[PDB]
Image (cartoon, coloured by chain):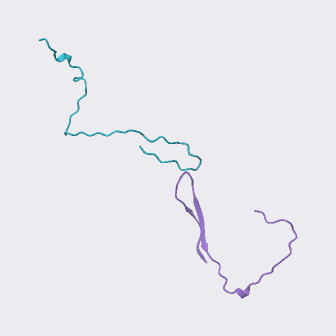
Chain colours: A cyan, B purple
């Protein structure tokens, strides 16, 4: 034999495997916690609103 | 003639401030205007006014 063997496969044996249940798979991400606003408000002042 | 005596009524919370109010409703009525009288322009000699 002048070609490769099974021991020359590295990445395929190390990547984790998860079972699939459909042709299309979905997942969700959390990009950020909020926007770049100020945090100092003052005495008796309602703070600004923020969203993720 | 009283509609309600003095009462304390809390308000909503729109910020880091605590608010409340005091209210009273009524009206005085004098049935016989001819049974009262008033002296006007009485002399004052002590200086000053009543304290705030």
Front-lying residue, A3 or B28: A3
Q: Residue at x 81, y 66 (%)?
A: B49
Q: Which residue is drawn at 59% across and 48% down?
A: A43
**Quarter of the image holding residue A52?**
top left
State the quadrant of the N terminus of chain B: bottom right
State the quadrant of the C terminus of chain B: bottom right
Q: Which residue is drawn at 78% across and 81% down?
A: B38
Q: Is residue A48 above or below residue B21?
A: above
Residue sticking out furthest to the left: A1
**Quarter of the image holding residue A13?**
top left
Residue sticking out furthest to the top: A2
Residue A29 in picture, x, y percent from top left = 34, 39
A7 lies left or right of B19: left
A2 lies left or right of B8: left
Front-lying residue, B44 or A46: A46
A52 lies left or right of B36: left
**Quarter of the image holding residue A20?**
top left
Front-lying residue, A42 or B18: A42
Q: In this view, does A51 lie above or below B18?
A: above
Number of numbered discs present?
0
B46 lies left or right of A2: right
Residue sticking out furthest to the right: B45
Residue B43 in picture, x, y percent from top left = 86, 75
Q: Residue at x 56, y 45 (%)?
A: A41
Residue B10 in picture, x, y percent from top left = 55, 60
Residue A47 in picture, x, y percent from top left = 52, 48
Q: In this view, does B45 lie above or below A40?
A: below
């Amino acid at each position: 034999n002048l070609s490769f063997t099974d021991q020359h496969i590295k990445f395929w044996k190390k990547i984790p495997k998860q079972k699939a249940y459909s042709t299309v798979e979905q997942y969700g991400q959390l990009l950020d916690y909020g926007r770049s606003q100020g945090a100092f408000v003052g005495e008796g002042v309602l703070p600004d609103t923020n969203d993720s | 003639k009283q509609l309600t005596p003095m009462m304390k009524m809390d308000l909503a919370t729109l910020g880091p401030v605590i608010r409340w109010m005091i209210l009273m409703y009524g009206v005085p009525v004098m049935y016989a205007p001819k049974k009262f009288m008033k002296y006007t322009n009485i002399k004052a000699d002590v200086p000053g006014y009543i304290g705030n």
